[PDB]
Length: 70
DNA sequence: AGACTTGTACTGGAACTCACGTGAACGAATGTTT
Image 1: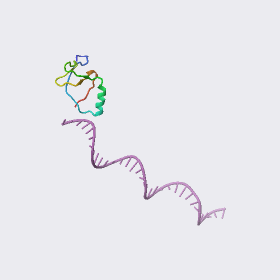
Image 2: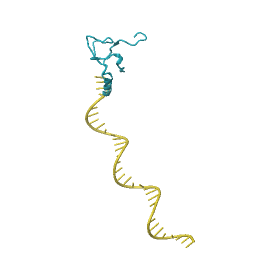
Image 3: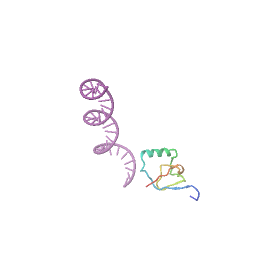
Image 4: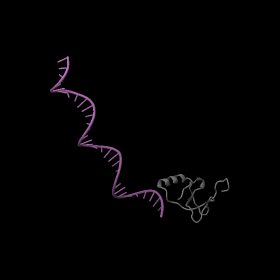
């Protein structure tokens, strides 16, 4: 972002779907359950920028969580 | 590829039980003292 501001736009990197136990996935779902929004290809959100791979449901970055990927 | 879940088998420790040992205590007989 411009100096002294929070990030506004995001660029997709990759899907990850392994490395979490069932309980961790349940807790993550409960945390982010309220903030999921349906994804419409015709009116994509401004904050998230995607290529050919698009999600079924998108969550605004302000309410999401950081994940470590190996 | 990778990561988690499920199923099978194994091994060590907990708990329970019996055998054996040791410690302390005691009534009766005997020996000693007065």
